[PDB]
Image 1 (cartoon, one colour):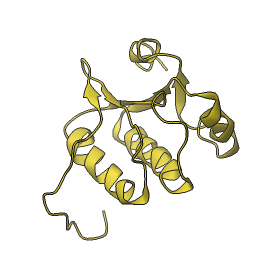
Image 2 (spheres, one colour):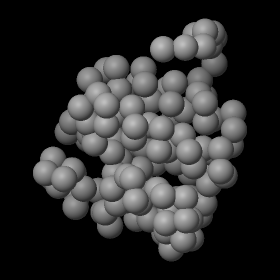
Image 3 (tube, helix red, strand yellow):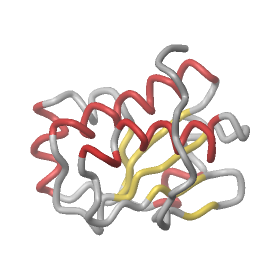
Length: 125
């Protein structure tokens, strides 16, 4: 709870998909500051409030991220972890894995090779 909800209707085209009860948030080349505070605000009302307790982040289509949204990624985990859910990542390319140690990303949020290794195992991890 906090800050005023003021967001007119001007969404572009969200890069993600939905799975059986799971949500695959597949960013490409747009994780700039203007899609970072709002990123959580979209996820909260597209998925989290909607009932979704399992998000995944594929990093295949993205070489890296800025320090700004790098902390929003954790924040989305913190919210889920408090709500009853889990969130994990997929195809963590070696360029992110190098920063994902150094910023405690993997050391907080789960990591898998594929979606499938996650999708049945975040169920039990």
